[PDB]
Amino acid sequence: GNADEXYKELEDXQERLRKXRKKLRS
Amino acid sequence: GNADEXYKELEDXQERLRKXRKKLRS
Amino acid sequence: GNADEXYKELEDXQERLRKXRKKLRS
Amino acid sequence: GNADEXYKELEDXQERLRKXRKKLRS
């Protein structure tokens, strides 16, 4: 519910998508 | 191509998360 | 940056993932 | 199976978004 908590959770999701783009191709 | 099209959608979601993190900062 | 804006954007992302689960299989 | 494993990860992200929306509400 706090801005910093959301910033970190959103970053984790963003990074997981970044990794899945690579995994999808490998 | 299914893999290619899926990759594009993952990257679009990744981009929206990056933009939302920018919006959280301000 | 507002709670309601974020709630709607997060829902849109959630629903896109819901749709991609189906598209991945079809 | 790659498609199956990818599906699971999409559903996990979908679940986290649902939980974050619940956190935004409160």
Image (cartoon, coloured by chain):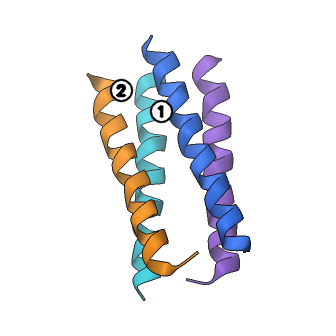
Chain colours: A orange, B cyan, C purple, D blue
Q: Is residue C22 above or below residue A20?
A: above
Nearer to us in this view, C18 or D17: D17
Residue D20 x, y percent position in the rendering: 61, 61
Nearer to us in this view, B16 or D26: D26
Q: Is residue B9 above or below residue B16?
A: above
Residue B23 x, y percent position in the rendering: 46, 80
Q: Is residue D19 above or below residue C4?
A: above
How far apart are the two marked residues, 2 and 1, measured between alpha carbons? 9 Å
Which residue is at 62% across, 84% downward?
Answer: C2
Query: What amino acid is at disc 2?
Result: Leu
Q: Is residue D4 visible?
A: yes
Considering the image in quadrants, where does the C terminus of chain C appear?
Answer: top right
Q: Is residue D9 above or below residue A10?
A: above
Which residue is at 68% across, 58% downward?
Answer: C11
Q: Residue furthest top?
A: D1
Q: Which residue is mark 1?
A: B6
Which residue is at 64% across, 50% downward?
Answer: C14
Q: Pinpoint the chain carrying mark 2.
A: A
Considering the image in quadrants, where does the N terminus of chain C appear?
Answer: bottom right
Residue C10 x, y percent position in the rendering: 62, 61
Q: Which residue is mark 2?
A: A24
For label 2, the SS is: helix
Q: Quadrant of residue B17?
A: bottom left
Residue A17 x, y percent position in the rendering: 39, 44
Which residue is at 49% across, 33% downward?
Answer: D9
Marks 1 and 2: in contact by CB < 8 Å? yes
Q: Is residue B1 visible?
A: no
